[PDB]
Image (cartoon, rainbow, N blue to C red):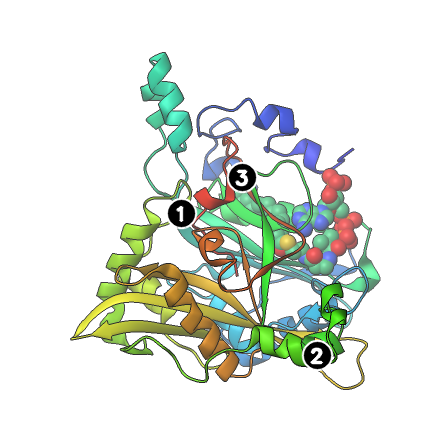
Amino acid sequence: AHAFWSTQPVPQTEDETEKIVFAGPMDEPKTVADIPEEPYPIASTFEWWTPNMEAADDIHAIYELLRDNYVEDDDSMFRFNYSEEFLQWALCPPNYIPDWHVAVRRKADKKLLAFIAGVPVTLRMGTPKYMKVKAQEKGEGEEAAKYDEPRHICEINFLCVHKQLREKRLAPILIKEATRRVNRTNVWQAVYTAGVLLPTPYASGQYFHRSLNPEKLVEIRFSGIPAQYQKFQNPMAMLKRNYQLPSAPKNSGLREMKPSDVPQVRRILMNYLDSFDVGPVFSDAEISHYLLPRDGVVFTYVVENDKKVTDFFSFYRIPSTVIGNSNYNLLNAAYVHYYAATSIPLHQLILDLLIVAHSRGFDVCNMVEILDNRSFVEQLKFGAGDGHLRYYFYNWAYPKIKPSQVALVML
Ligand SMILES: CCCCCCCCCCCCCC(=O)SCCNC(=O)CCNC(=O)[C@H](O)C(C)(C)COP(=O)(O)OP(=O)(O)OC[C@H]1O[C@@H](n2cnc3c(N)ncnc32)[C@H](O)[C@@H]1OP(=O)(O)O
């Protein structure tokens, strides 16, 4: 069934993954010296290219490839339009490796054909809580704890082949060359997400949406008007009313995050994430990079009363092109990022996220059912969407976990 994935170090079936009881590698140990020094071979008319994703013109070339060829729905209504500023932020965190950003171009004229990107992350990925209990019952705690230490791995994102080059087996070549470059840096696992089902996820969650501008969402056919609203004289008036929000935040002391908040925000975030089976470990530099506000890109607010930061939330912006509507160009979506609540209930924290995003001109707030996101779905009027985000590892055996045990947000 899978001419490429059957040759890779991943679990091959659901039934195999149901059988895994400890975290650890799939492949034999290898060394940097074992890995080919030269790029993987590619057709003579193509050439490998490493963009510099801090230089404006190279970022722009990658932006146009994704604008015109990245994720779109099956009805070709919406396609992601990540901004140039977003790509520089996502691709260049502290200690990033320029070599892990991999492109193919046509040699003759330099037309960009394909891309894939890796960034470093430190991830807790040892055996999950429920399987460590089973290990204790059986006298197998030592094997279950062998890989408990956080590991420096690769996160992969932005895999993209040009629409004129689809179904020619170019994606497997991109993945093999990414893998080589990563392994030449002595890193042997990766984490990735996809909306498609491949061999084999360790966790899967539904998407959720919260309408912020329901008249626009119905106009572009992102949303429809639900049937019972037809019992009203003015269905759209009642829909608007149902989703209305306050014009200003409700929590006293909410303000934008600043550099001096970095240590207190790292503390409350890490104490919270530690309770989940799979999650990141962030330094002060990575908390600054992923959470300090950047215009058009990442928005982060803290609750400070009486001089102490007790809570915070963040969201990020990804617009999508509206392909078929002749009245709107873009869908402006806000995605729930990291958060931590110590002084107020989580629903009260996240209502101010929705108030801020609406005030700033967003049309919808989206998220997946990771972290404690299920805890405010009903009260804050989110609804489940179509399909699911699946979490995968490369070269790591891992027991199936629930999405509410996943604390890693993928951009
Ligand atoms: C240690 C370091 C490890 C580093 C690497 C870790 C692994 C990283 C893995 C990547 C994680 C990326 C995370 C993200 O970015 S998910 C975002 C993916 N991008 C999009 O959906 C953008 C629009 N679509 C495209 O650009 C293409 O259709 C892509 C590029 C997706 C496939 O191009 P194309 O349609 O022209 O097909 P092909 O003939 O070249 O190749 C077909 C083979 O590709 C397999 N395929 C299809 N979709 C995906 C998918 N989303 N992940 C993994 N594999 C996928 C498929 O099962 C088949 O294999 P097999 O079934 O025959 O065996």
Q: Horizontal placement of 124 versus 241: left or right? A: left
Residue under circle 3?
35
Residue at the spot x=44%, y=42% of the render? Answer: 405
User: Which mark lies nearer to you, 2 or 1?
Assistant: 2
Amino acid beneath label 2: Met
Amino acid beneath label 1: Gly
- Farthest top residue? 138
Q: Is residue 306 above or below residue 27?
A: below
Query: Do the numbered discs 1 and 3 sit on residues whose CB atoms are within 8 Å?
Result: no
Secondary element under disc 3, as helix, strand or loop, is: loop
Q: Quarter of the image holding residue 258?
A: bottom left
- Residue 145 in sight from this viewpoint: yes
Residue under circle 2?
236
Q: Residues within 10 Å of mark 3 (few under 14, many from 20)?
A: few
State the residue in front, 55 or 322.
322
Q: Residues within 10 Å of mark 1 (few under 14, many from 20)?
A: many
Q: Horizontal placement of 16 versus 135: left or right? A: right
C-alpha separation, residue under disc 2 versus residue under disc 1 = 41 Å
Q: How many marks?
A: 3
Residue at the spot x=63%, y=71% of the render? Answer: 62
User: Which mark lies nearer to you, 1 or 3?
Assistant: 1
Residue under circle 1?
279
Residue at the spot x=59%, y=32% of the render? Answer: 9
User: Which mark sits nearer the N-terminus, 2 or 1?
Assistant: 2
C-alpha separation, residue under disc 3 versus residue under disc 2 = 61 Å
Image position, residue 154 (x, y; %):
48, 49
Secondary element under disc 2, as helix, strand or loop, is: helix
Amino acid beneath label 3: Ile
User: Which mark sits nearer the N-terminus, 3 or 2?
Assistant: 3
